[PDB]
Amino acid sequence: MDEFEMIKRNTSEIISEEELREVLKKDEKSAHIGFEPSGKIHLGHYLQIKKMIDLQNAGFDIIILLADLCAYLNQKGELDEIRKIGDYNKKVFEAMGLKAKYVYGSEFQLDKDYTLNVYRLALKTTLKRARRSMELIAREDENPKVAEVIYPIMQVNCAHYRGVDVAVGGMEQRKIHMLARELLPKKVVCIHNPVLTGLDGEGKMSSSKGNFIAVDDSPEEIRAKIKKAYCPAGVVEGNPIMEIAKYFLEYPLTIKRPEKFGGDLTVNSYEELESLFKNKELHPMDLKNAVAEELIKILEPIRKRLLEHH
Amino acid sequence: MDEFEMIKRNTSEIISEEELREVLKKDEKSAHIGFEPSGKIHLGHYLQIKKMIDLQNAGFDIIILLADLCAYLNQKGELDEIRKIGDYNKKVFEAMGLKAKYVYGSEFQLDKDYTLNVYRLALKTTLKRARRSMELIAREDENPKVAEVIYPIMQVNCAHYRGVDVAVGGMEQRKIHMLARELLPKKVVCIHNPVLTGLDGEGKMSSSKGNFIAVDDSPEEIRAKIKKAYCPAGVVEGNPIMEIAKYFLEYPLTIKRPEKFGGDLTVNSYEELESLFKNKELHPMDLKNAVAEELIKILEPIRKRLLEHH
Ligand SMILES: N[C@@H](Cc1ccc(O)c([N+](=O)[O-])c1)C(=O)O
Ligand SMILES: N[C@@H](Cc1ccc(O)c([N+](=O)[O-])c1)C(=O)O
Ligand SMILES: N[C@@H](Cc1ccc(O)c([N+](=O)[O-])c1)C(=O)O
Ligand SMILES: N[C@@H](Cc1ccc(O)c([N+](=O)[O-])c1)C(=O)O
Ligand code: NA
Ligand code: NA
């Protein structure tokens, strides 16, 4: 499995593969990702940090942008409190094993030269395009604010100012990234990770929607969250439990079952798991049990590293 | 005529009179106005500079903002060229007799503290309100840009950052000023001057609509412009020639006429002129002739001061 294929594993799209292949030849190459700081760090975050680790193992210098200023524009509170949550997020990401450079957006996003280019980009970006780019990111607001259309330009200029080779994010970011590729003289390679479904199956996993597993949830919390989750027999699309099996579990995987329900089942790949589940050969309750227990084990070192701090 | 009434003369509104009366008691008081730099300086500009002179004679420190950065946001070109036109505008205003402090917006509008407050205001300003405030200011654009909604916040923060007591502008500015009075902790007194009608009577006088008299137009140019202008007998509303008589001419005024059309007519006030014109006792052609000749004389020292430079 080449470095390209390691990077591509479990991504939704790379814009573009040819461009990534050219970046991979260089000795010095940088990848970055920004996060609005979040009170809880969940599996959606972890999926993305795992992708940054892949890039790091492929020789990329990694930068994690603690996006305090964009969080501010997106109505998450006061900068000082946002920054505090940002420092906590850094600790969690470090507990996930990511050794990287962490920078607050506001360290550079208020520089006169940054601002002037934001205003320069504002002349080239229609209100219509800016709002469309924010549809999956902007806080719900019946009276949308000017801040909502500043946010995407801020993000677009961020890739430019810092000179990054590769930008990583969830698929929600793809319209802002498309805008950046259209407006900036250097085209940034964009790696988009899938958006995980919330545990109740009704929307996307989100720290503000209460439908997530946090990386530091207790084992009994993880078990109860998964026990309650949407997981219809034979359906994989929009099935959060199957997504967790796909994106976080190591294979081969042994699903423990009572003898009276078939006894223990060993699954050599997610793909085999998907066949078993689609064929209603594997029952939701047994899938849930295996997913819960293997997820607890995967998250335990993170939870424990954070616990050692207390 | 008290200082208050001198200031109020020929204004469309003061927001608010009580607030202005309190400002007038202070020893130290500042008034400012911003202009997007303009290739030609016209009677609309002059009307506003005349109002600033009134404020100066009432003891106000006067600041003229050469609004290079807002002009940039409003698609008037590159900053360097905008700034050059700004320096020309300063010379014209000086030739009008205005001794004041001239500052380019960009000297302070890119400071980190300015920018942060712009983003702070962007959180409090809806897109809907921002666009409505720009309806009479924004360049025509079938695909409105993010820059259009940054502009009004920029202007709102300008009154705050510099600590001005009084903001002056045309009535086109009144929604931005209303926004500033709602959002800022110190309420700025707003003096709004009337918007002059264009010479063809179809819209407002504008340096981009070719419907203006420039302060440095030649006498034959002024004569031809006025000769062609909309000026229907007995109609004053939307009559640019009557507006020029109201806002620029000194009274008493002697309208020269051939004996066969009544001979010379002396008019002691604009109000008397309006009666004569409404009663179709004064013919458009004779009004035009007097307005043209008296306007030439009023503008001559300006034209001549600018000519001396060549
Ligand atoms: N939009 C990202 C945060 C983000 C990503 C990348 C960025 O460059 C910036 N930024 O500029 O502040 C911000 C999110 O939804 O969490
Ligand atoms: N508000 C949109 C986009 C969005 C999704 C999830 C979120 O957590 C946030 N947010 O809080 O910024 C925003 C929605 O509900 O789909
Ligand atoms: N809006 C004014 C220009 C202006 C007036 C006042 C101001 O404070 C600023 N500004 O902030 O740049 C700009 C015009 O239409 O010409
Ligand atoms: N574009 C609007 C507002 C406007 C009026 C006059 C103007 O000169 C400009 N302009 O050029 O910025 C803009 C209109 O035509 O009414
Ligand atoms: Na080498
Ligand atoms: Na005194």
Image (cartoon, coloured by chain):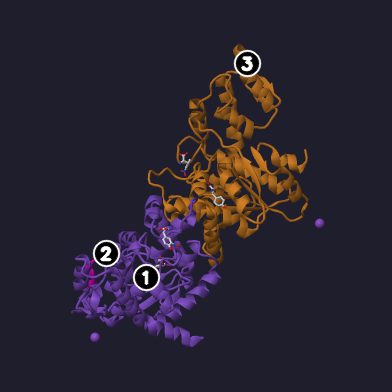
Chain colours: A purple, B orange
Q: Which residue is mark 2?
A: A233
Which amino acid is tagged 2? Ala
Instruction: Determine whether A38 is above or below B132 in the image.
Output: below
Q: Distance of mark 3 from mark 2, alpha carbons?
A: 93 Å
Along the horizontal axis of the image, is B271 left or right of A42? right
Q: Position of residue B268 (x, y in %)?
A: 71, 25
Mark 2 Cα-neighbour bin, 10 Å: few <14, some 14–19, many ≥20: some
Which disc is residue A227 wearing?
Answer: 1
Q: Position of residue B26 (x, y in %)?
A: 77, 53
Mark 1 vs ligand 2: CB below 8 Å: no
Choose between B144 and A197: the one closer to the eye.
A197
Q: Quadrant of ligand 5?
A: bottom left
In the orientation shown, which residue stands out farthest toward the bottom? Answer: A308
Mark 1 Cα-neighbour bin, 10 Å: few <14, some 14–19, many ≥20: some
Which amino acid is tagged 1? Lys
Q: Distance of mark 3 from mark 1, alpha carbons?
A: 93 Å
Q: Is residue A51 visible?
A: no
Residue at 62% from the left image edge and 42% from the top image edge: B192
Q: Are marks 3 and 2 in contact (CB under 8 Å)?
A: no
Q: Distance of mark 2 from mark 1, alpha carbons?
A: 14 Å
Magenta-tinted stretch: A15-20
3 vs 2, front mark: 2
Residue A19 is covered by the magenta coloring = yes
Q: Which residue is mark 3?
A: B281
**SS at mark 3?**
loop
Q: Are marks 3 and 2 on the same chain?
A: no
Q: Are marks 2 and 1 in contact (CB under 8 Å)?
A: no
Quarter of the image for the N terminus of chain A: give it: bottom left
